[PDB]
Amino acid sequence: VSVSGIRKVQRAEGPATVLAIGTANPPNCVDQSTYADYYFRVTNSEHMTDLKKKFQRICERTQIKNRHMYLTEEILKENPNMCAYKAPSLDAREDMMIREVPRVGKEAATKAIKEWGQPMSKITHLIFCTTSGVALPGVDYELIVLLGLDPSVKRYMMYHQGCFAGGTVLRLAKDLAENNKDARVLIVCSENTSVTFRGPSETDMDSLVGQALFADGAAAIIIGSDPVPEVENPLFEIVSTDQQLVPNSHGAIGGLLREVGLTFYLNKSVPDIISQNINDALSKAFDPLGISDYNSIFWIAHPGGRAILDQVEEKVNLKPEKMKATRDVLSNYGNMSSACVFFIMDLMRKKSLEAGLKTTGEGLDWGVLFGFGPGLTIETVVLRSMAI
Amino acid sequence: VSVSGIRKVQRAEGPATVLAIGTANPPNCVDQSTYADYYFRVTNSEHMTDLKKKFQRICERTQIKNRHMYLTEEILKENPNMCAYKAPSLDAREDMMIREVPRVGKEAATKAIKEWGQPMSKITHLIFCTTSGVALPGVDYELIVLLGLDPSVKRYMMYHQGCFAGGTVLRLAKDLAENNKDARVLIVCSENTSVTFRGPSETDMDSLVGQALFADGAAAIIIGSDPVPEVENPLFEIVSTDQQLVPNSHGAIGGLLREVGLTFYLNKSVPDIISQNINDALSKAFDPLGISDYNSIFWIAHPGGRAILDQVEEKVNLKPEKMKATRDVLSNYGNMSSACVFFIMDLMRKKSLEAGLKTTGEGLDWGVLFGFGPGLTIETVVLRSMAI
């Protein structure tokens, strides 16, 4: 009879906390030092001698050593339209996406659930983030079925978000967990290159670069406020989440869903863009916490490109090591879009534990996580580490 | 220095409240009593004499008198692939969607903002819901630009949600508003039939029925907790939001994004499905409030189809009038997907005011809002009306 009273007992009390992380990828590993050759071969573009030499340079300075990919040489053969630069292939790509995205996403969820140790039925919210794979019902539905989630789970299907979605899902999860007592959110970010893979064009260089960066992978995260003592194991607390649109940056990063799959472009200026606007976001997120030394906190940055990492580090004046975990993931998995920051988050706490550091954030109390994407969006999440 | 303290002062105190509603539609009005003829003519399907007579029956029992549509006879002529049953036309449809969805959505937002009376800069969150129009950055970005929203607005781009999204955006808005002090959420649900319009097929009857129900329209809603006395005008409070998946219903409602646009299917059993599962949702949402008489509360139901409304009303034993507002919108606008419930919400409070009733909900204190869609999802939102 009292909406005010309901609200008072319905809400959680503490900050949203990362309780478990799980990751998975398609088995197939593609070696970067030989991709230029593999790529130009399966695409039948050997006559583009100059472009090939060019693509080899790209893959070298990419600082990527390995990438997991659902697409095999066999799957490519059965799909000529996908090997071409631009040919009708949206239907075939979406079917692969619709089938693989939920799949790898489930593998990651299972690992997170096992770590978390709580029963399936306790998951109250489901945030599924993926670049594509459009169906109705959507991929979130399939995840529910494959995983066995409760039919009353509140769903949040985030399609075509962009490379910054890692921050998006955390920003959304914060509110879901904090506003509802006992709410336990399952985030599943599953990315797959099936929609973006295509042949080379002497006229579309941006598209050629993406063929060197994107990879496949999924990450599952359990998030909740008020962790149960001894039963649940808090890893990181979400302190604050900001989203910012950098003016005059639409042409920076983007793409369109077409009959020839997902196209995309990447301006050579994104590193400058991100670097010139990065300090305002840091100030907005750390001035309130009285933090001025950005080397005194740990980092987790989207690995959009090596140039980006170099620029930001150079501009903010960050010890090398601050970007080590981030570069480590980029080097072993490549650019898995929204899934990257969680692989880095996972890696950081894993390494911190084995090295005997005092906190999950490389022994430091505060840290920041960044997401970079379309329209040139910047997600800035402040994170508090957890002890031991 | 204290994450617990921050949380304590960062959160709102009261329940999320609807503060303003604004709607808009493409100018073009299509008369239902003559659509069968118009449809078979512009599609060049006059030879399907029997199917045409069949489609005329469909449009009659549809209980739809008018529908707003961006697509004109002229726009259809310039687009043959869209007039065909199934032909490559995804690119053309998406471009129309990308251009019109943000457009009509802005027109609706402006009306809501005017009513609300507060400055643009006060909008802290943006939830944009639309069936399609895939781009990166997305339609939400364009809305920000067209409208002049703050570059730090937190965005939530909800693509391909389904006919139940009206409840989805309210469920999401509840958390955003309630968990953040001063948070003011702008919801923009903009739907356009450009992706679903196509020619008739003697073999695809479900697709033919949809050609009779879907229409174009946009709705904007401002939502916030702790309304400012005298300055802000609370219309409805969001009490609770539930989402439910009805088992074995995947084939009920759905569709796939293809090279030929957005396809879809509608099982003849959805009315039975919705009716047989409707009481569990009512019980789950009203037993806690001690409400057993469903005629003692006001209604706002997605107008998926007349059969649905008839069935639910018959099963729940609802006075005729309970569904009057809902049928009114269905009759003047048709099925505008996620935008429907807000046109009904708007209509209900408008009518309640002019009739001199004591509350915005037809003079009753409590009410329910339902969303029906893919995988056969049911959104059940409990709403408290506001005085005078």
Image (cartoon, coloured by chain):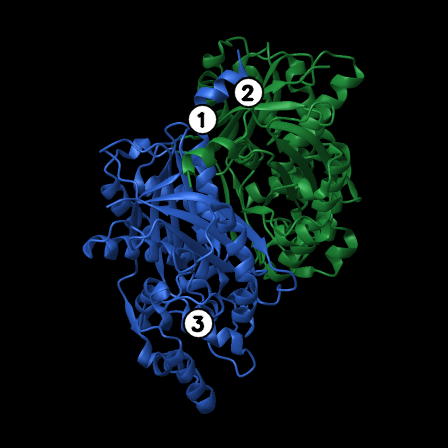
Chain colours: A blue, B green
Residue B200 location, x and y as percent? 62, 48
From the viewer's perspective, is residue B52 above or below residue A152? below
Mark 1 residue type: Arg
Mark 1–mark 3 contact, CB under 8 Å? Answer: no
> Which of the 4 image quadrants contains residue B107?
top right
- Give SS at disc 2: helix
Provide the chain ID for the residue under circle 3: A
Quickly name the residue at label 2. Answer: B312
Q: Nearer the viewer, residue B20 or B24?
A: B20
Mark 3 residue type: Asp
- Give SS at disc 1: loop
Mark 2 residue type: Val
Provide the chain ID for the residue under circle 2: B
From the viewer's perspective, is residue B14 above or below residue A168? above
Callouts 3 and 2 in the same chain: no
Callouts 1 and 2 in the same chain: no
Asked whether the viewer can see residue A386, the reply is yes
Residue B77 location, x and y as percent? 75, 58
Residue A114 location, x and y as percent? 23, 42
Q: Residues within 10 Å of mark 3 (few under 14, many from 20)?
A: some
The residue drawn where x is 60% and y is 50% is B152
Q: Which numbered disc covers residue A310?
A: 3
> Which of the 4 image quadrants contains residue A317?
bottom left
Quickly name the residue at label 1. Answer: A11
